[PDB]
Amino acid sequence: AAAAAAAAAAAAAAAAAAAAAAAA
Amino acid sequence: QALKKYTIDLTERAEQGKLDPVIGRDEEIRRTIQVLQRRTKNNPVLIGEPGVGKTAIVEGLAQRIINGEVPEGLKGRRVLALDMGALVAGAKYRGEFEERLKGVLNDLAKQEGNVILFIDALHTMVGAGMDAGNMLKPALARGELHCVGATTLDEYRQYIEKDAALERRFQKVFVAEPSVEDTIAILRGLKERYELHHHVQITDPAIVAAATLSHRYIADRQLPDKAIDLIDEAASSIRMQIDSPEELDRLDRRIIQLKLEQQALMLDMLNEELSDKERQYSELEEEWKAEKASLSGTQTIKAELEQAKIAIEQARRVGDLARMSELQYGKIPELEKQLEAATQLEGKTMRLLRNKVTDAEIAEVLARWESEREKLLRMEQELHHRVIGQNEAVDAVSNAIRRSRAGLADPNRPIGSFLFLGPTGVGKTELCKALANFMFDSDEAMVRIDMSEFMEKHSVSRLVGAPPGYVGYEEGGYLTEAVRRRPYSVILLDAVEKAHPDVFNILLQVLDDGRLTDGQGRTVDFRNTVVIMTSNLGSDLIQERFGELDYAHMKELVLGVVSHNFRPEFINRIDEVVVFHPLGEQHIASIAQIQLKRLYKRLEERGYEIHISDEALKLLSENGYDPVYGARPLKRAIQQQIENPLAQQILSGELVPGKVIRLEVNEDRIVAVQH
Amino acid sequence: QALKKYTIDLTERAEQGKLDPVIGRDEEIRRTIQVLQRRTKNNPVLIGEPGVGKTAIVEGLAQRIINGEVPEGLKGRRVLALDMGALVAGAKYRGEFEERLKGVLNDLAKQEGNVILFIDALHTMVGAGKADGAMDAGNMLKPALARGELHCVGATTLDEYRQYIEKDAALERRFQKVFVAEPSVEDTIAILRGLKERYELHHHVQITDPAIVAAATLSHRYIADRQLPDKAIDLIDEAASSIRMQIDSPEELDRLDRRIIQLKLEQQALMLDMLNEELSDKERQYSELEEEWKAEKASLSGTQTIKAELEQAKIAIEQARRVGDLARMSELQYGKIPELEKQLEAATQLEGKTMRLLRNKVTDAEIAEVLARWESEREKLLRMEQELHHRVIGQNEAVDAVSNAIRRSRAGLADPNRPIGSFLFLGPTGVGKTELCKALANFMFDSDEAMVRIDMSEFMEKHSVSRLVGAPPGYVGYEEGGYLTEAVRRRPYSVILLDAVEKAHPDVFNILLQVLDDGRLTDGQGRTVDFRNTVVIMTSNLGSDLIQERFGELDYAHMKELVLGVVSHNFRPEFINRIDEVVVFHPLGEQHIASIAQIQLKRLYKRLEERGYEIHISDEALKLLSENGYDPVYGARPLKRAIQQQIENPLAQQILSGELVPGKVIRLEVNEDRIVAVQH
Amino acid sequence: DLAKQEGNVILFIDALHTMVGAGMDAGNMLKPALARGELHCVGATTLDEYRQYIEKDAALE
Ligand SMILES: Nc1ncnc2c1ncn2[C@@H]1O[C@H](COP(=O)(O)OP(=O)(O)OP(O)(O)=S)[C@@H](O)[C@H]1O
Ligand SMILES: Nc1ncnc2c1ncn2[C@@H]1O[C@H](COP(=O)(O)OP(=O)(O)OP(O)(O)=S)[C@@H](O)[C@H]1O
Ligand SMILES: Nc1ncnc2c1ncn2[C@@H]1O[C@H](COP(=O)(O)OP(=O)(O)O)[C@@H](O)[C@H]1O
């Protein structure tokens, strides 16, 4: 019999940006 | 053996003849061979939009290797292709993509400088999780790998200018778009393969017509691919129509129904009628079998023709002497001439039917998924199908359209450049709609711009396009999205006189260049569209002086008025300013009649049979009529004074669908009757 | 054989008739076969919606194969279906599920395009088959893409094809966008008519075809997610099981059984009686109804068995059409079909004599019961006119005018290309305008939040169309969508208010004139949304000075005409003439004030009932609230704050003082300028 | 044993995602009896798993 081996499980998250006008 | 797990021996496939005998492109193939025999940076990339057959370019390179047209570094190599999606998709954990990737490199070093690699979706390999480019960095750099790219120019400038090792561990080889004639020769090379597969023949004028219509009525797909799809789907449709039949189904249902009737009746007559219909069905069936046997013989002799061509290519590779002249001079002309005997024989015998796919089948496949010039010959009649009066403007516009599609003037100058005057409401916009309709597609498949509004500098910044880093940016000007999403439409300019005169400069750049640079750095062309400018400056000049005054001198008079108004540079670039006179009271009455026609159409959509007094029509035409505005007050006044009391009486539970409903007059109004 | 392990032969099931007869779609199947016998791009995939007989398209193609309704190249072929979890049944090791898979591939190599497999959800089979030290089906059958042993068919949705299929090159150039269209009402009805008898077999009932078409009607009107024939199938079959439950009822049996066991308890206790006789009567009644119930059950049992016999006769004569027996055709037809139909109808009229407690024909009323568990014009008209008077008080001229406008709207004999609502509502503020919009939502759109409140008071500025509608970005109201057009893209079934049209601009009237003519409206983003399922309402206050002034001793029609002339002074008359009707809201003088203050008093009474209090108001206090609460300029708003102050501050002042006892009639007597609560 | 019971026993297993996987394991083993009709079970879930683990596999629809 064998054992339930542990994993590594690479995960990821993201970013927004932001653009900004000028008035004139 | 990940090569067995992930790669495709294309040399095996073309060695077994599985692949396209790809035609042309020899300069680019040669530059790829130049790149593939360097010492370092031994990797070409292929830059072109997908569907131009960069895959097929590598395929034809592999076929040349099968031929052995290569210099002395490539004789004996094995070209193998690979995806990145086959590697990314198995990434549960850390380090599972990359075991596959390194085992790939172990097989690559294991074959010891003998394998040429192909990888498409290079911009995919940028992002997988560092992830992918850095493990391939040494073998891309140290000559121990011969990667071949395939991607698009946008993805090149988006992805591949980021990692410098991703830049210079590849090399650009530009991939161009194939021409019209080269597509024709390509399909000529591809004709026999298709005719072998779909068991039928192909009209070659229908091939060049398919090329013409593929450029004409398709925007997205391009060559070779779109004509491939057209000819394949049309050949499949014809093969289905041959491999059925309909009259046999009608006769079979007829004979089994009369068989059940005669079985029920057991006066007769039905044994005789059944025997006649069975004889006719047997005749149609035997004709069907004779046609299928004829096409079977034609396809077998066509496949033997292709096998003779493959055999004479094998003789060109191996070098048998009498086999070359024997196979050529015997087998090619006699099999082609009895294939043409089968062609004229099946032109005789296919009745119920054809096998040679015509361009009407191409029209089916195309419009599902040809009287243009001759309709343009009757284009004035088309415009007066819907709009009454203003004959001269219709004539001049048709002159411009004939000059356009005949192509005499400067093609870098736009199609329609027309300033319009006079009082509105008579159907100027209706002329615009029907003009875009019977000219190209539709009434309101156009662009309308309210140039009454725009009077200042910021107004110009609106309709032109805001400069970057400012307010109105990321979806261009008012104009620019409107044309860039509409490659074939009509631009409308209402109240040109209200604008500040600087927008006329933008109009002049339109009329000269046709490409117009916005604030978003991209030029949106106008050369395949029509600009219509409209105004109302000499409205009363025409209203006071239309009576027995001509077209030309009154045009010149109001043209002088415009010269008092507008720029001499601007009126220089005008093709023609038409008059747009007020027509008459009876013609505007007739336009009201056509509004009654579409009204009665909508009543029939509800399902009512409603008629009218013609005196009631005269009272209608005298309700909202004004010379100052046109028929639009007449339109809305008639619409209100009909839709309110009539639907009032309908919701009063008076009108029944299917009665004589005569719109009789009141003393000043209109009542409906029920008879 | 590995083909015998975990593959689902559709041709075998259709040869056994196990698949259901699929009706129609012949253009789709024809164009599918067009895609089938191609040289390149040889694997079709049904792009559609979840639930639309896409599986049934494949199985109907297999039925055309068994019928021989196919071209000769498809003759002799094999339509199979491969299950995933069947292959993942007994295999988790290092290369055993994958060994089974590759053996299936070797059997595909054994047949060489003879078997034409089907596996739907290609994107699922590509981007979800995760395995540890082992592969998927996607990258193991991606060789079979470029090996020609795979003429397989797919099925997906419009979005996931684009996610996980269009991005790959090989998974592009082996595959064809075989779009499948949304079917009609009547074709769905025809499929229902074809498959009605199968359900009548399974569920022991009968089905009304008017109920079929009305079920299709209310399903297409009301049911959102479910599709065709999915919602029709589910309504029919769920109603069938409902009537089956009604078969396995009754209820007066339970009435009499509880009665007899109760009187049995009583008589067993009393061991005067009379209850022996009462028990004997009720037991005889119960036994009679019980035997009647069993007789009806036997009647339906024989009826359903002979119905199933009729369908088995149809199956047998179709087998005779496939095989070709001579006397069997005419024998089965002319004997078995008319006699079983006429004695099935004899049993049907026998039931319709004896169906006292039971039914078997699923009516449209049963479908309405299912749907309520899940007509229009005149009822909507009358109840609309009724519901006008409830929330909004008074304004009976406006009641009748908007009633006329809704009537001419839902008639649809006006311009249908105009939007539903085009309204200018003139009058002062306070006056139920927002309440009228919400009541219009409350009955036309049957809810509260079917509205989008936007005033045009904020849109005197030049950038009205940008923030309102959608623009070239750099703004805020772009990733939000916008103010108006993209909220209609959120809410296509709504009511639009436009307050303060006197605060306008040239890019207000023009956008509104495109609304008035079109309904579809050009945003910045380039995606017009129609407004012809929605109501557009404007309000102003321009001639409302005259409305506040001279509503007394003046009429409604001439006042409306004069204030329409005033709007023609303010606006361009070409703008204001595409509106359906411009109406006038009068100042709400006395009884409207008394009613709405009474509404707020009653909800106050309600919340203090939740506290536990019982309060009565004096009408003199109501008079002082009418004086203190209404102003000629604003109306309900000083009434709200006057109620607030002059009621709730002494009220809660004394309740928190512990002065008032729960359970007393708390009369709101008057002070000199205030209201006193007393305890009596 | 559930096959032996032959419609007599009616199953009810809520939190149906656990039947989708229970540590190959359970979804790939039961999903035959699901997609064969021998199972006569009853599900019960939160709306979250109905969006996530149910509508995604349209093979269970
Ligand atoms: N020189 C050529 N001779 C014949 N056909 C060609 C030639 N170049 C391209 N084509 C056709 O172009 C078609 C496009 O197919 P693909 O090779 O998939 O397209 P592509 O140009 O490789 O871009 P993608 O990314 O693969 S869609 C092929 O099927 C070829 O038949
Ligand atoms: N005839 C009426 N029937 C019922 N409540 C009324 C009537 N006239 C005014 N009201 C109330 O007066 C109060 C004032 O609040 P609002 O509804 O915001 O003002 P008004 O109805 O909306 O007019 P506007 O458009 O807001 S200026 C609300 O409680 C209204 O219900
Ligand atoms: N015209 C029709 N003929 C036969 N079956 C139909 C028809 N319309 C709908 N169906 C049924 O609808 C069900 C759903 O099929 P489908 O739309 O392929 O599922 P999904 O959308 O989940 O892929 C099928 O089982 C099929 O029996």
Image (cartoon, coloured by chain):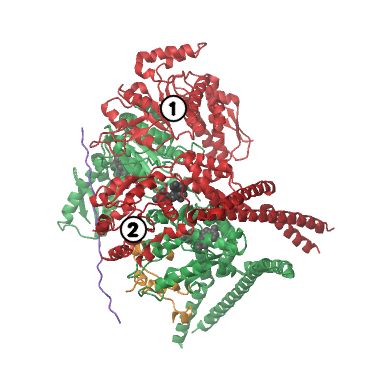
Chain colours: A purple, B red, C green, D orange
Question: In the image, what residue type sits under mark 2?
Answer: Met
Image point 78% across, 61% down: which residue? B262
Image point 58% across, 53% down: which residue? B327
Question: In the image, what residue type sits under mark 1?
Answer: Ile
Mark 2 C-beta closer than 8 Å to ligand 1: no
As drawn, B200 above or below C500: below
- The circle drawn on residue B84 is 2
Residue D1 point in image, percent of width and height: 44, 82
**SS at badge 1:** loop
Residue that sits furthest to the bottom in the current view: C271
In-image side of B88 versus C654 (left or right): right
Residue C516 point in image, percent of width and height: 41, 35
Chain under disc 2: B
Residue B139 point in image, percent of width and height: 27, 58
As drawn, C449 above or below C137: above
Neighbour tally class for label 1: few under 14, some 14-19, many 20 plus, Cα within 10 Å: many
Neighbour tally class for label 2: few under 14, some 14-19, many 20 plus, Cα within 10 Å: many
Q: CA distance from mark 1 to mark 2?
A: 47 Å
Chain under disc 1: B
Q: Nearer the viewer, residue B539 or C392?
A: B539
**SS at badge 2:** loop
Residue C269 point in image, percent of width and height: 44, 86
Q: Work out whether mark 1 precedes mark 2 in sequence or the reverse, and give the earlier one.
A: 2
Q: How many marks?
A: 2
Query: Is residue D34 something that shows in the picture?
Result: no
Q: Quadrant of residue C295?
A: bottom right
Judge depth for marks 1 and 2 and give the one in front. Answer: 2
Q: Nearer the viewer, residue C352 or C664?
A: C352
Residue corresponding to mark 1: B415
Q: Nearer the viewer, residue B45 or B460?
A: B45
